[PDB]
Image (cartoon, rainbow, N blue to C red):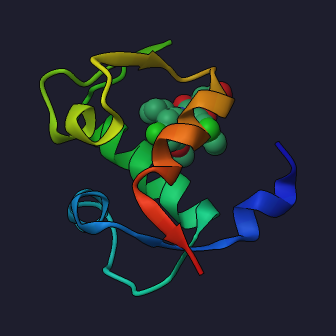
Amino acid sequence: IPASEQETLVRPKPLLLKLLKSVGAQKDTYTMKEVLFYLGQYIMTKRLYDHIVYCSNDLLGDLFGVPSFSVKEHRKIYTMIYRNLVVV
Ligand SMILES: CC(C)(C)S(=O)(=O)C[C@H](C1CC1)N1C(=O)[C@@H](CC(=O)O)O[C@H](c2cccc(Cl)c2)[C@H]1c1ccc(Cl)cc1
């Protein structure tokens, strides 16, 4: 995963936007750096993470389509996030 990916510009779909709005200011266009931080912050503030995030109990699970995932499998995380946004 190249660092340049963090600079890419994206627009979250409605359910992802709902999640992001609980940790950051609403924007019409975000960088992937922003999306990753806000999602990460959401997970930490809600203590869904202690390397496993448990989200069967949360909107995040509905967004990702999984009951849990590892914080270390970055490829899979990127793929899960991208189902929930549109590139601009
Ligand atoms: C402290 C923080 C800045 C808020 S954070 O680093 O984002 C916290 C979250 C963790 C889920 C709660 N998080 C991490 O702890 C670490 C884990 C690691 O070292 O590999 O980085 C995660 C990360 C960062 C960038 C890209 C990806 Cl795909 C994952 C990264 C992570 C981000 C987003 C998701 Cl969906 C999952 C993990």
Work out which quarter of the rendered image holds the C terminus and state it.
bottom right
- Res. 56 in view: yes
Residue depicted at 54% across the width and 65% down the height: 34
Residue 25 % position (x, y): 32, 78
Asked where in the image residue 28 lies, by quadrant, the reply is bottom left
Asked where in the image residue 1 lies, by quadrant, the reply is top right
Q: Is residue 20 left or right of residue 15?
A: right
Residue depicted at 65% across the width and 31% down the height: 74
Q: Nearer the viewer, residue 26 or 56?
A: 56
Residue 9 to residue 19: above or below: below
Residue 41 % position (x, y): 39, 47
Residue depicted at 12% across the width and 24% down the height: 57
Q: Is residue 28 left or right of residue 61?
A: right
Asked where in the image residue 69 lies, by quadrant, the reply is top left
Residue 68 % position (x, y): 34, 16
Residue 12 % position (x, y): 40, 68
Residue 18 to residue 11: above or below: above
Give the total of numbered labels: 0
Residue depicted at 53% across the width and 52% down the height: 36
Residue 68 to residue 58: above or below: above
- Res. 50 in view: no
Q: Residue furthest bottom?
A: 28
Q: Residue furthest top?
A: 51
Q: Is residue 59 left or right of residue 37?
A: left
Q: Quadrant of ligand 1?
A: top right
